[PDB]
Image (spheres, coloured by chain):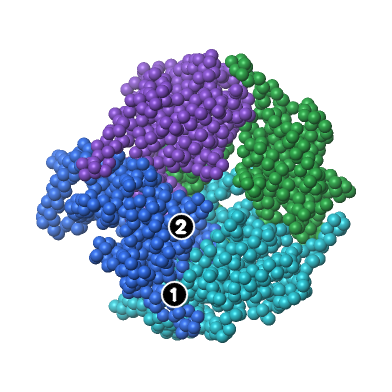
Chain colours: A cyan, B blue, C purple, D green
Amino acid sequence: EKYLKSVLRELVTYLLFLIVLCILTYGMMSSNVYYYTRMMSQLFLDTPVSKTEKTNFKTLSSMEDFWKFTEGSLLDGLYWKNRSFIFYENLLLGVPRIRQLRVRNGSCSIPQDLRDEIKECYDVYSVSSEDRAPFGPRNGTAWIYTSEKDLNGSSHWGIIATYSGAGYYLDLSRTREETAAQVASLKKNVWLDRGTRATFIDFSVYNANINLFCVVRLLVEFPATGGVIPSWQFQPLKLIRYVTTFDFFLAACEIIFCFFIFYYVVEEILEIRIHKLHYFRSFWNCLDVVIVVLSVVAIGINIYRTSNVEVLLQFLEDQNTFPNFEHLAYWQIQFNNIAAVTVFFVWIKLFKFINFNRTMSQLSTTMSRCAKDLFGFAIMFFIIFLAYAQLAYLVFGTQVDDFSTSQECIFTQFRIILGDINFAEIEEANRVLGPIYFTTFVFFMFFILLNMFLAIINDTYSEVKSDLAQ
Amino acid sequence: EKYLKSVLRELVTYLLFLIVLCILTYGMMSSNVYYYTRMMSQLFLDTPVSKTEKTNFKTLSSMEDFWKFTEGSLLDGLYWKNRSFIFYENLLLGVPRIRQLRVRNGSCSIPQDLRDEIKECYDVYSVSSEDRAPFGPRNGTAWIYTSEKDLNGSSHWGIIATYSGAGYYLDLSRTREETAAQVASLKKNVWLDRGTRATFIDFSVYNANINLFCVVRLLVEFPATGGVIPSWQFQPLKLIRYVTTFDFFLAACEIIFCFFIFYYVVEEILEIRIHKLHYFRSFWNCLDVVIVVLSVVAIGINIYRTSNVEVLLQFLEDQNTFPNFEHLAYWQIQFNNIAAVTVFFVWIKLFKFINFNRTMSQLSTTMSRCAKDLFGFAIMFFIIFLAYAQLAYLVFGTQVDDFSTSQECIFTQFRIILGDINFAEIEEANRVLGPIYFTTFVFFMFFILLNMFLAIINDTYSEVKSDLAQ
Amino acid sequence: EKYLKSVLRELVTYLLFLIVLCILTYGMMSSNVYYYTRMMSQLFLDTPVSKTEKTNFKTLSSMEDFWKFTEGSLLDGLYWKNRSFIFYENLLLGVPRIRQLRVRNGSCSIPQDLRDEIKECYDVYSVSSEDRAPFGPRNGTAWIYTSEKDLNGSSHWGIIATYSGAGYYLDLSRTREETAAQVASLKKNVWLDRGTRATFIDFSVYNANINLFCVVRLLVEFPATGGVIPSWQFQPLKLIRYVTTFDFFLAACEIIFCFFIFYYVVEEILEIRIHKLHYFRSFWNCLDVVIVVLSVVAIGINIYRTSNVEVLLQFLEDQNTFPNFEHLAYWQIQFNNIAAVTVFFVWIKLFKFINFNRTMSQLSTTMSRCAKDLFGFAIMFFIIFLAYAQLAYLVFGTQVDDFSTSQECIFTQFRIILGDINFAEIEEANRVLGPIYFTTFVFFMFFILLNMFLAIINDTYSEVKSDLAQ
Amino acid sequence: EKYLKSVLRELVTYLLFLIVLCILTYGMMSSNVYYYTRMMSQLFLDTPVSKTEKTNFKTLSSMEDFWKFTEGSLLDGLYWKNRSFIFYENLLLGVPRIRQLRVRNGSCSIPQDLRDEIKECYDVYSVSSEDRAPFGPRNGTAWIYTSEKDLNGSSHWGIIATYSGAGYYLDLSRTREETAAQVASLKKNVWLDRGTRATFIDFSVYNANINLFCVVRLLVEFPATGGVIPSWQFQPLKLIRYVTTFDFFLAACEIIFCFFIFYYVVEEILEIRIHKLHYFRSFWNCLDVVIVVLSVVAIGINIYRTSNVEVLLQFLEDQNTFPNFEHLAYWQIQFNNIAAVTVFFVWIKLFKFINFNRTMSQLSTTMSRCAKDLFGFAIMFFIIFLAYAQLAYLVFGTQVDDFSTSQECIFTQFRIILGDINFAEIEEANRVLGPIYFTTFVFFMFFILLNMFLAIINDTYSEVKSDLAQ
Ligand SMILES: [Ca+2]
């Protein structure tokens, strides 16, 4: 009877922990936030670059389109008629910033055959090929290289390369007329030319109705082959924490969560000190360790982020400067990811107390007894899966977007297995190998290989049911 | 022999009942009705707001677009050249009505940090923060709050909030010139401003060729974050019933259905009294009780709806007023839902007489024998399903429309399992966690977990067949 | 040895027959024909109604759009600059024809409540409500009713109704200027009004390069609820057969096919005369009877169609008339359908000689021994399938296009099972019952019920393999 | 121990070989190449033909659109302001070339019935119907036929026909003004008329930043039924190889790969000389032979291609000519295809050393024992699959794009099985047979026939596990 009562006590404690965690994670969420970013992104990406034009920021194709956007839709969205409100609600915080990364002329070598017709070549962006010399009129921060440290920047993982936080930057103005003049001055002096490899536009807004910031980042990359590759980022933040009663309730819930985390840390360490050799012999102990580690990491990230609020205080002293909220947004994204993973893994631990009756124990035994063969056939299946992915990358890699990178081929093959196919592009890219690849993949994966998993599961379930009937 | 004859008599009676119910439910449906609403919705939602503009009602983005629609496409669709026929057949009944819901300034608290730059804040719509004071010129019903009781209104479940039936309303006119003047007067005095949270446009039409009304409701919501969220509703009604011979035939069928339902009620009550100890132990008795309860609820709703025809009589006395058919449309929708569910559950009861031979009995035994294990593994499977849904909500909640609400995540995961995927948006929202979530979900759900249902069914079928073979 | 050699002889004869049939059916096909209709349909449907307008023929919405098409894109497509070639290759044969079907005023009864505001009502199209009296100026065939017999017409199965071959028709002219004048005269006198229920535009072209006709039919329906429902039909024909060497080769193949069919008829009749009582005890005999009946029907249709070449001869005598090729196109479509079905069923008969070794016999025994239970569970599964379809029709019937008709619901549910879903529209139509219907359908159909077929097949295969190992 | 250590040595050697091959195949790929072709194709295809027009090169519909493209978007893309750079990076090499294929008047025979109205007919393109006589002004190479040998051309496999390398060609100029004059002169003299059957536009560019050429080919076909069928081809080439350090590293890797291939060839020949009769009894020996043959073919193609760099040398002597890189592009495509297949098959051989423990051996034995029955049921299943495909071709062949060719039907049926359906077009093409075909195909294939594969696999797995358990 002691075992059942102890299990019930553990179940009740874990249920309380689960309710606390769910309350926290839904308190840090709301429907108000999705439409915030939806309207912001629509305004800044979906609006045509100009009345006559049709291309938006989403469909930029050249430097001329980027200049039209910068002098056009961007200024329309940013400034609303001394203080701007991106809508009638969202105040524009301070000043926007524009930054570019540059590459040296001669960072690549032209073949000796063509040196008579081609004199200048610019390599793809890299830390080695980066340009750090003044150009243009050399008047101000837009024409002089500023290091990452002096710019208080950080690296950004772009579509085709990873970019540093340094470059040539200009701080725009509070009003539309001044910003337009600055942008026109930049364009006249040819700010963007052959050496440009990336450009960033950063600005943040604040919504007092719901007490949420929004950090915006627009990146346009200029590959060595010509054209542009636009991208965007809209990240809401809650820098100010305690403004309402629900905020204090969530603070209390967070304190309770920290108490629970410390209690679990102590409990797990106590058992580790005795069973350390065989502690990882059970999956539940590994799950408990993962949960506690993730929760501790989340707590540490939260503590670090809460002390970074001093950047907001610096901005509030003088509002004519650029508010650097990129680090806060990055750490908020990291915290959200870690909290989501912790919640997911806390949910999975519910299987520990799910053996109510003989049926649940039957199913759990079937699933545990089936893992050894499932892993082996997973290796076997994924060998062929990766062979097919490599063939697809080598065949359609340069033509089809779905196969443009070795990682994207895996996702495309998963989608094809599910039923989300784009066979027209595959057939267009290669009229002989495209159809052969598609047909053979579909056959040997959907029709045959996918059924080995189910055969293993079926045999294991039947064996377990026959055995446990005793 | 008595058992077989009694079962045959029951089967014949139930076949007659099913035929009557199907006749009723298909008589209350026609192909003419779908194209009615199709043309109405194409006229009002799909037409461009103006000749130069591209945005329609479906794609409104701001208060300016809403004003352009109200002064533009709405008047074009409403008035066709004293009486308006909306294509050439649908008489416009009475006048339309426009109603807005409002919020008080100061219903939220600004953080003390930003009180020097922001003075006014309006909270999200709620009954507590609702505004009930006059504004603007204070001339008429458009500038004074009218309660739900005095407005004969009712609540509406919107996209982002549930709204009351009160607010500030104006009754438009019969002709285009008067309505345009009223709308221009509203716009000049700034009817919509920071405090607006919702707006409604209501009107109904009548088609004499097919004898059907159409109650229309256009709702535009104004979130606290800016922008607009349009929505619509086109609900045909049949207030006048006995016109043609088929209508009298359907009335006779309804009388027969009522007699059948009374007979079944008496039979079920007698069986409950006789076999109180075994009634709820059988699934068929539960199905019979569900069917009888749903049919009684449908009959009650129908009786209430017929007594509600008095609203049409009030309108017919004076045609210069607004016909309030919202309640009739709501109850028609409820009746349709109840009747559809009753039909569905009446169809399922055919399984009672489906045991013709050994094959059908074996199949039914197999289905009823694995229900115990199917429910347990359904619990086990849906624990992981909801864990994945919660992770998806916490990760893509603020970026992807498909995961914008906790309920939307479940439907999106069902669609992903089927094969309807939107992986591009998932990868765009999170380039690391998006692919991991998608790949792990697909693997652990489609490839492995979904096959446990199949293993259970296969093992149970084999066991049942082996047992019943002897 | 006797059985093996007789089977070998039968297999050789049937392989020759199959080769002949495949040769015929692929000789009556060519890639040249798909692009013929593709260009015709792109020219007539896809092109905008006018330079300023955006609506196509596919997106007509009112009588004004239809008039603009008739005076606009239609004349541009028809006439190319006495003889017109709809492209630089396809001669326009004779003149086009326009025909409308009409309904009487007062074919429905207005409710007594509204008789003071509505005086005229036109019912949906039917043979009883059809109008047969002159209207308008009463000058010519466009304003007088012409019966189906005198018009040499036939019924057409439209989208919302089935239409007769009678009505009010006008024969257009050979040149653009005359046709435009006729259409303008029709429009000025108000040819289309409240009574119109359908309109037809018929014309045919000839392409001498590939020796193919193309019979075109554009139908626009005018429901009693307003609006228009466009539809089209492009049917290539081969009236002139024996021109090239391949045509004579195909004639020889057709003669060989008739000889084979007579031989098979004689064989089957001889077998029936001996085993008439138990002849239908075998599936292969039923397949043979089906094949022979379908082939005889195809031969009869071909003989009827060849005699119907006299219509072309009548047209060729005077080219200033309307070539009535509608019957030839209808019979060509019927012949193509019957030939396709015959080819499909001839392919299936290849299973008779597929028992090469023990593996094929094992699989055939498994499939035949499984049909008894597969049919029973098919009935069981389709009862629930039809219950769900009826619920979907009653719930989303008036809002969603995919559920607009009772037959559309079945196809939509099949598509949903496969993975082709449109959940957004379902959720929009009903925000409570939509999600419930979708989720419950997906669960109980894909997760559970679809696996009973698979369990039955697996058990039968295992039993057959265990038995035949003896 | 004797077997295990030899297997370990073989595994290590094959792992080294696999790493070398993967290094080579990923060194011949880069993300920079996908966006190269992406920008090129967006510039030339997606760009509107003119400011007023909407048709692209992808949506050409007639000779007028082709002329507008040639005088419009093509010249805008080609020439950027003596030397042109398609972007600010990609130099235009030499001059473009325009070529056309032609057919004789009278290559077909008109029926005697219509010879009084039609005088000229042009057959579909073929080597027999090809025209080879001068036309037009007869001034220069654009109006005289040049054979394939004298044009240094080669055949091209188009959408509706295979085309020779001969025809009437004009070499365009280096500057926009001269090319526009030449194109206008061609258009004025009616270069394209009834006899035209195909047109090609060829040009290549070079990117010094990434050292990659791009051979471009735009083909517009003119069917005998009218209209145009555009198509395109963008193929990057690495003609110049030894420039950077990574290039020398890849050369060393290629030398190592050649040594490995020679060693494997010797090893396999040694075993063949001994096991001549039973060498093919093992699947692994067949895989080794396939790998060796494919690698040798790839090496031969590479040797042929490297010695073919002389074409670039000829062009570099005089840059005022047309650079004929078509053969180099063709052979690069062939080499890429063969290398991809070799990589795929090299990956599959990893299964030989995958028998680590009892689980992997059991899975491999299950897969091996299945092949006998799986092949038989594959024949059985594909008989019905091809019957359905033939029926679909005969029914929807002339109406639906997905069924336009007998090969397209197979791919469309695979897609339908997966879940990628276009049921709307199928139902539109045939309203009776379309739904029947779709429903019966889905049922008999997805619900029933696809489960026999799984039944076989499951039964074999259970048998193998029971046998090997003891
Ligand atoms: Ca699927």
Count residues near mark 1 (Cα–Cα under 10 Å), then give few for <14, some for 14-19, many for 20+: many
Which residue position is annotated with label 2?
A: B68
Which residue position is annotated with label 1?
A: A209
Corner quadrant of residue A125: bottom right
Q: Position of residue A229 (x, y in %)?
A: 64, 61
Q: Nearer the viewer, residue C374 or D52?
A: D52
Label 2 beta carbon less than 8 Å to ligand 1:
no
Q: Residue B362 carries which label?
A: none
Residue furthest right as drawn: D317
Does the image show residue A469? no
Nearest to viewer (mark 2 / mark 1): 2
Label 1: chain letter: A
Does the image show residue A110? yes
Quadrant assignment for the C terminus of chain A: bottom left
Residue shown at 25% from the left, 39% from the top: C110
Count residues near mark 2 (Cα–Cα under 10 Å), then give few for <14, some for 14-19, many for 20+: some
Q: Vertical placement of D34 versus C247: above or below? A: below
Residue shown at 49% from the left, 55% from the top: B55
Badge 2 amino acid: Lys
Q: Which of A454 and A398 is in front in this view?
A: A398
- Disc 1 element: loop
User: Is D157 on the left-hand or right-hand side of D93?
Assistant: left
User: Is A54 on the left-hand or right-hand side of B193?
Assistant: right
